[PDB]
Image 1 (cartoon, chains in turn blue, red, brown):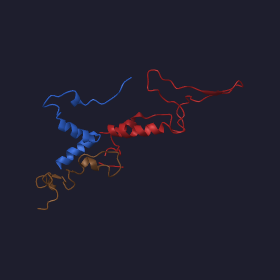
Image 2 (tube, rainbow over the protein chains, first blue to last red):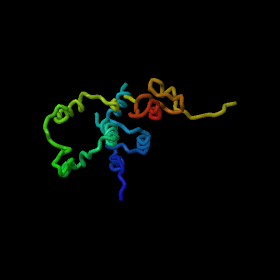
Image 3 (cartoon, rainbow over the protein chains, first blue to last red):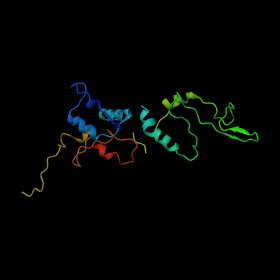
Image 4 (tube, rainbow over the protein chains, first blue to last red):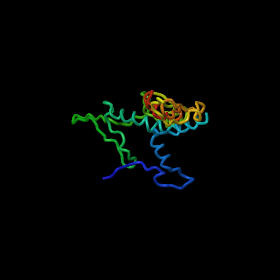
Length: 49
Length: 88
Length: 49
């Protein structure tokens, strides 16, 4: 009898300069697709571009 | 870099091939500590005895020997549909 | 006189096409920044939001 689930680090930690955790940033993440490190890298390259 | 390809794609391919009609044996329980293959032989009182798994050594089929170094090209010189940015 | 509807939009003049943003649909829409993998073509678009 259990339920396996994902626990975001933001749902544990909330140190101010360490882990951004504003509800804004939270729901903005809720909008995001699942990500690979390559996806994130591509995003970073795009903002750079 | 490649981990999302293996987990989020290649694993599903394993899951389907896992059901193909001719994959009839059970190969591994996920427990290196205990697992042994089930072992059947055709056999008759009239004296015949053919094991289904047997160890005859290297054979012409070219499948008896494994080169583990295959991991290296996989971890390095091999691209994937999931990396990268789009690919159907 | 005769204005139909007055809306509060994001300012296209500030958030220019130079920002890579596109405000024509009513929302910011940056192409090819975040984008899901493993989805059929044209499934990327919501991420543009």
